[PDB]
Amino acid sequence: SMEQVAMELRLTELTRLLRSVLDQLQDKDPARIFAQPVSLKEVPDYLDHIKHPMDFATMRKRLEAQGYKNLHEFEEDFDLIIDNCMKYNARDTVFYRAAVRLRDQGGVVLRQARREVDSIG
Image 1 (tube, rainbow, N blue to C red):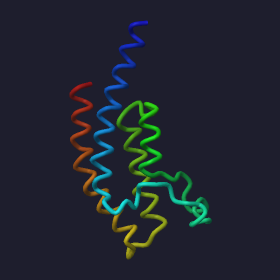
Image 2: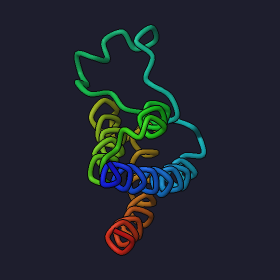
Image 3: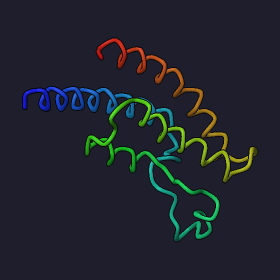
């Protein structure tokens, strides 16, 4: 149906806007602390601590499959990245600190992304 195509075009254009958002957020992580999944070979206890691991590569795979239906879903995954790290790592660590800085800087980007998604529909 044409209605199904039109919905698919809207998902495509959301995907485009979320790719730009993802790029901008990842630039706020110049150390690449959040680029890849935590390795269970190197942190074998991780899944005892953190139930839903997340990282930028995993988000990018979901994005390229058009797997985010709305901005809320994408924000949920970004928040997991930050929140997971702030639980596993202590306040005095480079990891925790990196997460705080990513959260603070990413807020700016997400605030305007929300206006854009609402505005364009």
